[PDB]
Image (tube, coloured by chain):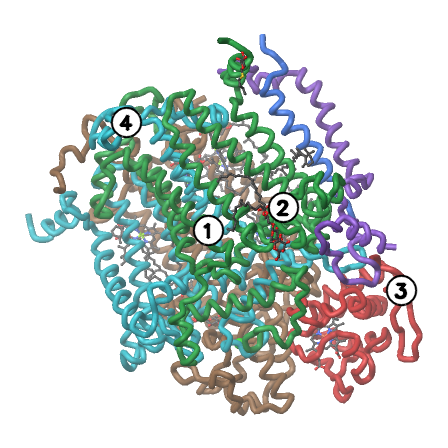
Amino acid sequence: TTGERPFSDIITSVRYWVIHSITIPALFIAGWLFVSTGLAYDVFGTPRPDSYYAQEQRSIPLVTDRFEAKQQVETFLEQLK
Amino acid sequence: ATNRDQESSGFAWWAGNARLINLSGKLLGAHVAHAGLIVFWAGAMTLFELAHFIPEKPMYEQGLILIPHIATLGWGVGPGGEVVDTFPFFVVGVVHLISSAVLGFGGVYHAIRGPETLEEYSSFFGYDWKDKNKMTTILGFHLIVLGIGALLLVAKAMFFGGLYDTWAPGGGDVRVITNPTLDPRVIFGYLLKSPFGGEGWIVSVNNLEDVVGGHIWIGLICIAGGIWHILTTPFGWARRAFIWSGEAYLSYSLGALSMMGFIATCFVWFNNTVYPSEFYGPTGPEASQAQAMTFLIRDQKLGANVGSAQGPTGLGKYLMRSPTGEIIFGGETMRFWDFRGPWLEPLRGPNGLDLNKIKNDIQPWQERRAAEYMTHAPLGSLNSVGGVATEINSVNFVSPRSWLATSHFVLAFFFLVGHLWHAGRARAAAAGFEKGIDRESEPVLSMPSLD
Amino acid sequence: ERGWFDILDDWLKRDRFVFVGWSGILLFPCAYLALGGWLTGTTFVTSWYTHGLASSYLEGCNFLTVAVSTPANSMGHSLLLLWGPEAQGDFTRWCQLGGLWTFIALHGAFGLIGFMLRQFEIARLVGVRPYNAIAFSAPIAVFVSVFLIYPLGQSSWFFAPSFGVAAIFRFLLFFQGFHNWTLNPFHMMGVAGVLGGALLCAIHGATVENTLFQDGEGASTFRAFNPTQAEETYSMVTANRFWSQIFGIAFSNKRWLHFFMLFVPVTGLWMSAIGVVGLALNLRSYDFISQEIRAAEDPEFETFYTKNLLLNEGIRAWMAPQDQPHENFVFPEEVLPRGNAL
Amino acid sequence: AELTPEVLTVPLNSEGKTITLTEKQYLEGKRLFQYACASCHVGGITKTNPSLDLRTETLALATPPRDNIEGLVDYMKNPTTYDGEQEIAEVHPSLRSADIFPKMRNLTEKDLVAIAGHILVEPKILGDKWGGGKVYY
Amino acid sequence: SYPIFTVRWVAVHTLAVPTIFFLGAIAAMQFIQR
Amino acid sequence: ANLWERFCNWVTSTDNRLYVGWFGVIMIPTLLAATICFVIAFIAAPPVDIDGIREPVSGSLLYGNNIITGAVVPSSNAIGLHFYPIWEAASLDEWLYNGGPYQLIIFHFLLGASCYMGRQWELSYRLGMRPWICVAYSAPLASAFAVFLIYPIGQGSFSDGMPLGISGTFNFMIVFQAEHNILMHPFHQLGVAGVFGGALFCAMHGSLVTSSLIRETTETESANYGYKFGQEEETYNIVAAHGYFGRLIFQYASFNNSRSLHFFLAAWPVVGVWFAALGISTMAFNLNGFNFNHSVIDAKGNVINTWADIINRANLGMEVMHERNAHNFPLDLA
Ligand code: CLA
Ligand code: CLA
Ligand code: CLA
Ligand code: CLA
Ligand code: CLA
Ligand code: HEC
Ligand SMILES: CC1=C(/C=C/C(C)=C/C=C/C(C)=C/C=C/C=C(C)/C=C/C=C(C)/C=C/C2=C(C)CCCC2(C)C)C(C)(C)CCC1
Ligand SMILES: CC1=C(/C=C/C(C)=C/C=C/C(C)=C/C=C/C=C(C)/C=C/C=C(C)/C=C/C2=C(C)CCCC2(C)C)C(C)(C)CCC1
Ligand SMILES: CC1=C(/C=C/C(C)=C/C=C/C(C)=C/C=C/C=C(C)/C=C/C=C(C)/C=C/C2=C(C)CCCC2(C)C)C(C)(C)CCC1
Ligand SMILES: [Cl-]
């Protein structure tokens, strides 16, 4: 053994479950809200179902320049009306 | 806790059911409880199928494997396989479900409440695996039961409404079987057919008279052999050839079941008589022939002479000759010319497909049937997207013939592995070295060197 | 001299549940970041602006179709640093431009270095020979040749493999269609090493388990072994006689046997890596010139070699427009290669 | 892009009257098309006769025209060949032949409109993919 | 007798804490409609 | 000591350099027949009309093949699943044209290899061994049945069995992908885990045992001379190996029981290859890999491509080109 408390000891202790009956659902709910508020879309820049295309276009907004790539994406994002 | 840990029994928990080998009373419970599970599933699955069943859709578009078994026996269906009454499906489900509680009850009682061993309690129900007389007697009882079971199918066919006959004149119908084939040259001649293409061994049975008469022969044979094995004990040649132990007897049955599972795989894949395509969908050969039929019909309506249309390879675009001369469908389906089905046979003459019948006698119901089977070919993805692997999502379909054939190949394969596992272990245990080599008696150390 | 360096060394090498070591300063951040980037990317990040693809659970992909995709072909071989001139510190743009791909590949490369330093470090403390580290050179040769050298020979990172299940399947099929990679003898050697390695794994395990000495009374033979016992737990002599009489030849030296088990899969992976280095430059084993000369002149000459090239030609024409959107391939129906009817 | 009333507006008849479907009608049309039609018509082609597809341009040149709601609803009651010369209820599913095509027995008039609407809207969404076959997959 | 905050404690939570958050995010995604 | 008992004692003798046994009585003639036919056909057989369209494919060395492109070509699609022994042909020239040799080779090989598995059981019994080495061999054996017998049955023709050649194997794999999307089937995925895992654990076990060899030699000699065949004592320190690998990961991720370690080495690749074999066997009945083609749709209903759709494009290219003259009707249903 290496000195740390055995895992079977910990996860059958009431105090472990007093603490983790709160921390585990709290993290789950934070993750749910990260999606349900729509925050995940805006942090990562991921399209919503209604923003892959403009209403009549069928061309991908593909990045084609290396050093103006940032402006190209911003321009593609404007053109969503 | 008799034999319920590794120290007392020698078997770890992951081989825990091996602790039951010499505990006939608990072993009886395990077997009865398990049969309840089988009967439970049959009852429950039928009810699930019925609840999800729409009579206007073909069975094969609905993921049904049990209702097609009931419909084939003549319950609930009329001409063309149309469902006329779903109540028999209901009855079959309910009765199996109710019976499973009886079996579950007895299983749980014998498993945890009743006597662990039966030998002290009753010498009729007691047994020793090494008692060759008692084992063949128990075997004999169960052969008589199986024989009655085969005779119940005959009773349904001859006296209680008949069977669904996909071949019946007028499109398929329930029909009472009045003259079952009894000629043993026919019945046993099926057993000596080659299993290769155009022959098909017993999978090729194609009429209900042979099906019913084969079950008459099987019924008598099982009853006779059952009486034989009650009254006799294994002969000397038999005694020397076998291992006589519980695990050995298990291993023989595992071999037998694996063989039966492989046969059932081919039965559902090729046979359209006892697995009517009305209920199960077309066979793979059937849907491929149906495509050729569909486009022959389309192109002939446009004015093509399909008899003389030369395809790109030089073989007929629509029709060609089999290696033995018969007129057959062309294209890649040349491999399927052994297919026989009621929608196709009216076009068949002595030389195979008959060009005059093709030109003049193709009825609209045949065009309908071929377009239906061509578009319900047994191809589809694991998530039940129907069609070739390159098809787009839209059609939720996998044929029952694919489900039944793949499941039973997998089961038969693992049961062959189980046979090898337990036959090899039974042999080693009988001879006494299934736990390893005795260091002081290592057989190879007493043998001359190879070189 | 017990300065701060030696005190730090003491703490790093404590016998704890997870050993750390000096190597752990490199290993743990880089491994954790590479794994966290893959999970972050496959959960939340799109491939819409680089590939025209959805690629995250957020977009509706499943475990088989999510990926962290390669950057757009227009990025070339850019490091795509978060603070570099393409993303310019903008985390959201960085994600949209494929910055997570180089993030994962580069932290992964340094993570792998760190894992192999860990094998050396622990081996030197415990006192064993470092053959586990040496065997691990083969996974490293594979990773570096496929994920780094191969795209560096090509036009851009875009043609590197993307980090996903179905994306890797696309990579296998691209290599068949464009490189005829099944024909490459360096791949063939790798196949032999992998399949022969699996074979050796199965046969050695089964042979040990079926030549065991009866060292206990239970029907479960696992208990009859003690890690400190001096005796072999199975009979090398009976094993040798069995395979000599079944197969003709057998192992008789147990040290050779286990060196060979190291040698076979490690050598195989190294061979496959060399072939991929050649594919970086399109230096393929694509054709047999003698077959092509004959088939060009003799329209009745047909082999499985010529049949497979027709399949490769189908792959290229039918997948290129979607798989290479920056090229803008417009292939009208009439130019697509197809057999009769299909 | 969104499924808008503009997308859901389709010709009702040959005289140029339009009708605007609801999203619920469109989605019901999709489900019923899958139920009764897609085994042969997945993606707007026709597996048992690939010469005839469900592209609006193809439907416009049918006789009588089928590129509008009334033409399509009539087709599902009494289908004809492309030139209108022959009635093909005996080999194509229809209300007239619901006895031999049992899936048509539980379609109501409202359903035929929704199926028709799906067939006319889908090309406005999918372009060439609708009726184009494997080339556009 | 035992400590609470060890290296193993840190290693466990750097993995387990984001896992639960991600599982909640992915659970929410199953109710997104197009 | 009558002549039958004498013959039985020789057949089952543990003193023959190669064990014969009752399985070997079937094994030896069938494997000899398959081997001799294979060698002759590979060198000298004329072209074979595999797909039944009078378009013969050249498989042998003398007809323009090298080692990589050569094959014994499957029998004709016109034969389908019919039995085609030499005596059903009007002549040897007919039999060769129609791929007769393929049937003779695989039927004798499958019989011989099944008897090879029985022979592994049989010798273990004669030597007092445990009996399950043959269960491990059932994994590669099941696979041979899958590509030579089961897949032909389900598709209805030995012309869709695997060719007996290097490039023929590749052809089989590519067409399999087009028709079943095998890459997306979990049983092939479990098979890849089986052989990638098996290769990994092979190198793992080899490296750990080699790392813990007990010093018994000088540096100028092979450490392999430190082990002597038949010696009673182990040749490496499994405690040192476990002490290294436990710290590499953590202590409870490491084996210290050689028996359960070696059982794991047996089980992992054997189970994985069983699934691979069952993948081929169940895709023989057209239960194909996952189909996510056009699974992701935007708010308007535009298809949003995934990597699955890119795989579909490659599959389509394989589909439309394979057997380019063999299809007259639009669906490749078998
Ligand atoms: C069909 C599957 C099946 C069946 C019928 C059995 C049956 C049995 N097992 Mg086995 N076993 C199985 C699967 C099965 N097992 C599996 C998957 C494993 C691996 C985990 C094992 C591992 C194992 C070990 C290690 C042992 C057994 C033992 C036994 C026997 C005694 C069990 C006991 O005393 O528990 C007592 C348990 C209880 C009293 C708790 C509840 C049990 C009841 C039966 C639950 C029934 C619930 C049901 C809904 C009630 C319906 C009532 C209604 C019909 C009226 C019994 C005959 C034991 C044995 O051999 O004894 C000699 C034994 O040691 N089994
Ligand atoms: C009628 C069939 C049958 C019967 C009565 C037996 C009976 C026995 N077997 Mg055998 N066996 C069989 C078929 C059978 N076997 C088959 C088909 C195989 C090939 C796979 C085997 C392979 C086998 C091996 C390798 C061993 C046995 C052993 C045994 C003995 C102990 C069994 C036990 O307690 O397992 C306990 C049950 C479990 C531990 C549960 C297993 C869980 C399975 C793998 C899950 C399967 C997944 C499921 C189908 C789907 C997923 C479910 C999930 C989604 C929830 C017992 C005498 C042992 C023995 O030799 O004793 C003498 C032994 O070592 N069997
Ligand atoms: C003979 C067995 C068998 C067959 C052929 C079928 C066939 C079918 N079922 Mg049924 N069913 C079965 C047994 C079977 N089922 C059992 C045992 C149950 C209770 C769990 C059910 C309960 C059930 C329900 C509730 C439903 C079905 C449905 C269906 C249909 C769709 C199947 C599907 O989409 O699967 C999806 C495919 C899988 C889930 C793949 C399973 C992979 C397994 C886990 C691998 C196991 C391998 C092996 C056994 C383990 C070996 C381990 C090794 C170590 C030895 C199809 C007709 C559906 C339907 O349409 O109803 C009308 C439906 O809703 N079935
Ligand atoms: C094959 C299954 C099977 C077998 C071999 C046995 C055997 C035994 N049982 Mg068990 N048992 C079973 C299933 C079985 N049982 C079931 C399903 C239940 C729940 C109903 C029970 C509930 C049970 C109890 C409560 C007791 C036993 C007892 C016994 C012992 C004495 C029985 C006797 O002498 O009856 C004499 C024979 C008869 C009375 C003839 C009965 C005929 C049946 C009821 C009519 C149907 C016959 C027909 C073949 C059924 C077809 C069923 C098929 C469709 C599935 C004997 C060892 C006794 C015991 O253990 O003593 C300590 C005891 O007290 N059993
Ligand atoms: C579950 C069914 C079953 C089982 C397990 C048994 C078991 C037994 N029977 Mg019984 N028997 C049965 C049903 C059964 N029988 C029936 C229904 C009848 C009436 C027909 C008989 C009539 C009977 C007689 C007359 C005798 C036995 C005997 C025996 C014992 C020796 C078995 C043997 O050596 O076979 C080995 C099989 C052979 C030796 C057959 C020849 C080998 C050929 C070449 C194998 C061919 C395999 C091939 C793959 C076949 C494929 C299908 C084929 C038809 C084309 C054994 C205890 C013997 C005994 O000891 O009686 C007390 C005996 O003399 N049985
Ligand atoms: C296969 C058994 C089919 C089913 C199910 C459905 N259709 Fe069909 N369709 C089929 C064929 C062979 C044809 C050509 C008929 C001919 O000879 O002209 C058609 C044609 C149509 C058309 C006409 C298309 C055109 O371009 O003119 C329409 C509008 C049509 N089919 C619609 C339709 C609907 C709504 C279905 C479900 C109720 C349906 N079809 C099913 C084959 C099959
Ligand atoms: C021994 C043992 C075991 C096993 C057990 C078993 C297996 C048992 C079985 C059991 C069973 C097998 C049971 C059953 C039961 C049943 C029931 C209980 C039923 C009921 C029914 C009902 C109630 C019905 C109803 C209805 C109707 C009538 C109508 C329709 C609708 C409905 C459905 C509602 C185990 C492994 C655990 C372990 C331990 C030992
Ligand atoms: C019902 C029906 C029918 C009929 C059927 C029949 C009549 C059957 C029979 C069957 C049979 C009649 C079978 C048999 C079988 C057998 C077997 C399967 C055997 C086996 C054997 C073995 C296994 C052996 C082994 C061995 C050896 C070889 C050596 C020595 C040792 C030993 C013993 C181990 C028909 C088709 C008409 C129709 C449909 C329905
Ligand atoms: C990128 C980046 C970063 C990082 C991040 C991170 C680090 C993250 C992490 C993350 C994580 C760390 C996550 C995780 C997740 C997890 C998950 C999501 C899981 C899931 C699972 C499952 C789902 C399971 C399943 C299963 C299996 C697998 C088998 C067994 C059974 C079961 C079924 C259970 C930073 C900020 C630095 C910077 C920027 C960039
Ligand atoms: Cl065709």
Q: Colour of chain C?
A: green
Compared to residue F46, the image places residue F311 above or below, namely above
Could you say which disc has been placed on residue D6 in the image? Answer: 3
Could you say which disc has been placed on residue D106 in the image? Answer: none
Chain letter, colour red in render: D
Q: Look at the numbered disc 3 and give the secondary structure of its residue.
A: loop
Q: Residue at x 24, y 65 (%)?
A: F36
- Residue toward you, C11 or A33: C11
Q: Residues within 10 Å of mark 1 (few under 14, many from 20)?
A: many
Splitting the image into 4 quarters, where does residue B85 fall? Answer: bottom right
Q: Position of residue F45 (x, y in %)?
A: 30, 73
Compared to residue A55, the image places residue B124 above or below, namely above
Tag 1: residue type?
Ala
Name the residue tied to disc 4: F235
Quadrant of the image for the C terminus of chain C? bottom right
Name the residue tied to disc 2: C63
Q: Residue at x 72, y 35 (%)?
A: E24
Q: Colour of chain E?
A: blue
Whole-angstrom CA distance, mark 4 to mark 3, is: 81 Å
Q: Look at the numbered disc 2 and give the secondary structure of its residue.
A: loop
Q: Please name which of the two marks, 3 or 1, marks the residue nearer to the observer.
A: 3
Whole-angstrom CA distance, mark 3 to mark 1, is: 51 Å
Disc 1 with disc 4 on a shared chain:
yes
